[PDB]
Amino acid sequence: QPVNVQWQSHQVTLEQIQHYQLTGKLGYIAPDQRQSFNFQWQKSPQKLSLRLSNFLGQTVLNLQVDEQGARVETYDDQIYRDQDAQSLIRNLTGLDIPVEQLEDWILGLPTQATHYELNEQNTLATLTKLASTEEWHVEYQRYQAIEWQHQPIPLPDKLKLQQNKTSIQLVISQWTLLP
Image 1 (cartoon, helix red, strand yellow):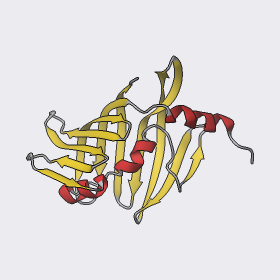
Image 2 (cartoon, rainbow, N blue to C red; image 1 turned 180 degrees about the vertical axis):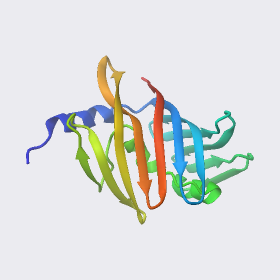
Image 3 (cartoon, rainbow, N blue to C red; image 1 turned 90 degrees about the horizontal axis):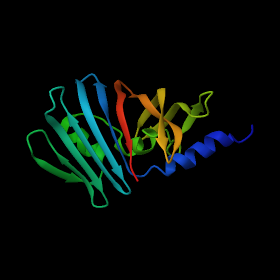
Image 4 (cartoon, one colour; image 1 turned 90 degrees about the vertical axis):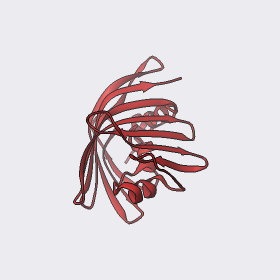
């Protein structure tokens, strides 16, 4: 089996995309709760902001991740801090969102220690990741070509994540790639 040069080159380009915004819908289904959220995801080097709001626009949760750790402002404006964003969100809301892994998956990058399959366009089709006893199955349902430094690059615009009984369906509205 030869190295897939197109896939490896795509990875290097994705690794350049360090400052960006992303908006869309996040559909959450689990045995304990079902939710339909607007999401606003803002990424910069070593930093992440994620706002979830309800279908009427009111804030459900605001997450900030930086070098100090994770900070969540909850729906009722209580403030909580801890070291791991996924664990903190789960303890405060019951929602299981693999925030750390999504920093790679949302762009179409794999994490380390993962299995995956490519599509015929040499980008991710499906991926599996065993993380903290959760076996995540990720499906890249659709890509959209987005301009990056004057070149069209495929980025996910429909992505589904599932582990156990929990599924997260992301549907993208707008990628905004920043200098």
